[PDB]
Amino acid sequence: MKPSEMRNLQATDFAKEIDARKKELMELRFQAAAGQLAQPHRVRQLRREVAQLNTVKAELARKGEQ
RNA sequence: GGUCAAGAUAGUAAGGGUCCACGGUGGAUGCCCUGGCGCUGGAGCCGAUGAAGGACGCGAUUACCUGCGAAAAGCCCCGA
Image (cartoon, rainbow, N blue to C red; front, side, top):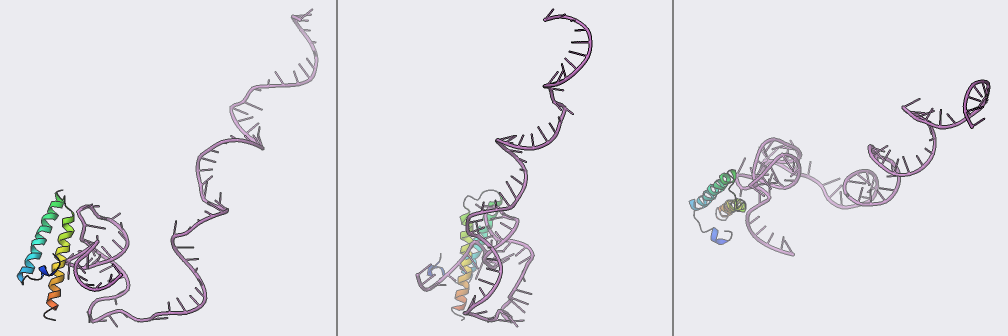
């Protein structure tokens, strides 16, 4: 979610995690359009989640290739 | 008391005037500060790593502002 249990993943295993959230985020976007969003907090959570993956994939790119 | 005569004089206000009472309109005066001005001192350049300044966006709901920038009213570390 946030500490060291996030960086264990390989190359395509990072792009995979993003894609699964973007898809969920879109299913929620469609849910919003048809008056079905009972859990709006889920929206920001996934956006915070995708941000974290994208931030870390840049940390590890510099904590190796310098 | 009655009739006639000769006199003289009053009230009525359609509307108006002055004063009084009570309102309405209006935003002066007073009180206040959420905002300004001056002087004294501090500080004093930003930009091809893309500035000043903008456009369009980012909200469960978002028209304006603010804050951001497709990682979008926020993501990571250190300190309080």
